[PDB]
Image (cartoon, rainbow over all chains, first blue to last red; front, top):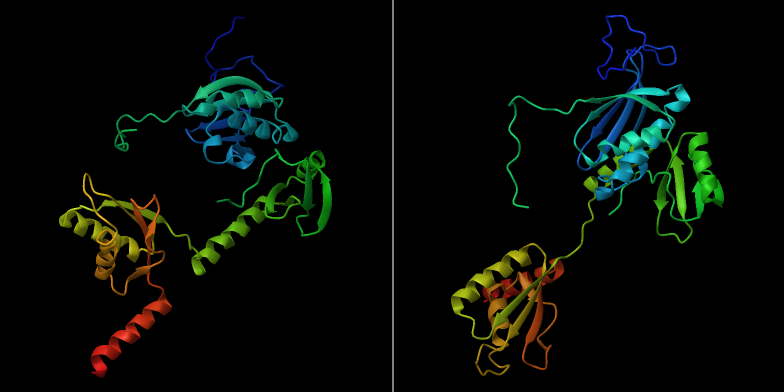
Length: 137
Length: 191
């Protein structure tokens, strides 16, 4: 067949398998790319925490956490703890427009993990709560 | 300013005096050999004492890294020891108007009440000839407003070949205060 960019809906039967596992079963890599930090947490299909890493947990301080090298370092630290539990294929769910939004995705690949999808779950309200006032800096 | 958090897998110094999680002294070992123990037992290294010339690092579990600082959050709360003194500066002019001298004299009263150090400097007024007789009479005029609260730390000096005078003020020390108090009572009550 051809190749579609839309994810295979669970209900309808498909033929796309990864290591004999359906798309639903693949573990999920929740990335929260903030402006001053980047936390990464890998979970299974049944929401079971397997690995957690962040720039702070890798020995970075203050303004070094909001860089692209600290997010990549955090991906290698989470892709090395989850590869010992039998994780190879993951579903990336990026949340945030921070510096370590794409650099953490590269770090997960530098740990032996293969990314099959890229999901964006950045919080966008349909007017809800009021942000802080604009600054003059 | 430091925190009891893991340093990570990046060590600056090649030789470290590693310490066991249970407090056993592993002994000095190569930097590469330190990371092997962080994976073999999945433990994080924290620098216990920077001051010592030989690098000292202790590897403990994440729960052990939380309990440590969780006690440093109480020791400082129970017995806080913050003694740094901020230093403030003022640069006046001999011909400074009284109104501006009363506003700047009230600013010094807030600094002396917060146990700050006030560096006061006086300069020759614009196109004004004056000696150090009335140029040094402003310190005595400022200190008089604070009789007991403030006292000289340093004394007027010719910082810049005599054109300018610099002095430092401080909040009166507890002991000194008591002495001032004691003296005040005798003058009026005994009479």
